[PDB]
Image (cartoon, rainbow, N blue to C red):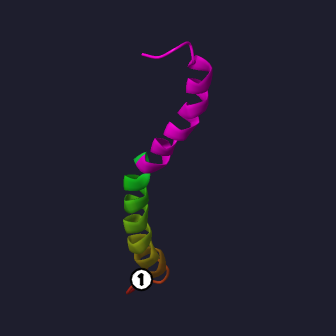
């Protein structure tokens, strides 16, 4: 509750956007896992064990 400084709010909000990145952090962890696994199946899914 401060003076009429909403003009600075919308501006400072851009700093909160950082969350958008921290939110995908988990997905980045999942991505990593997916990649690691894929690199295998992706390679083993070429000629298989016949």
- Viewer-nearest residue: 8 or 40: 8
At 45% across and 43% down in the image, what residue appears?
A: 19
Horizontal arrangement in the rendering, residue 11 relative to residue 48 (left or right): right
The image quarter containing residue 12 is: top right
At 41% across and 46% down in the image, what residue appears?
A: 23
Q: Is residue 39 located in the magenta-colored stretch of the structure?
A: no
Q: Is residue 44 above or below residue 23?
A: below
At 48% across and 49% down in the image, what residue appears?
A: 21
At 57% across and 18% down in the image, what residue appears?
A: 5
Judge the density around disc 1: few (<14), some (14-19), many (≥20) Cα neighbours within 10 Å: few
Q: Is residue 26 above or below residue 9?
A: below
- Viewer-nearest residue: 12 or 26: 12
Return the x and y of residue 29 as percentages of the image width and height. 38, 61
Return the x and y of residue 44 as percentages of the image width and height. 43, 81
Q: Is residue 35 above or below residue 47?
A: above
Magenta residues, start to end: 1-22
The image quarter containing residue 10 is: top right
The image quarter containing residue 41 is: bottom left
Horizontal arrangement in the rendering, residue 32 relative to residue 9 (left or right): left
Return the x and y of residue 31 as percentages of the image width and height. 43, 61
């Amino acid at each position: 509750a401060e003076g009429d400084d909403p003009a600075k709010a919308a501006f400072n909000s851009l700093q909160a956007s950082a969350t958008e990145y921290i939110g995908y952090a988990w997905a980045m962890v999942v991505v990593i896992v997916g990649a690691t696994i894929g690199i295998k199946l992706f390679k083993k899914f070429t000629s298989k064990a016949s």
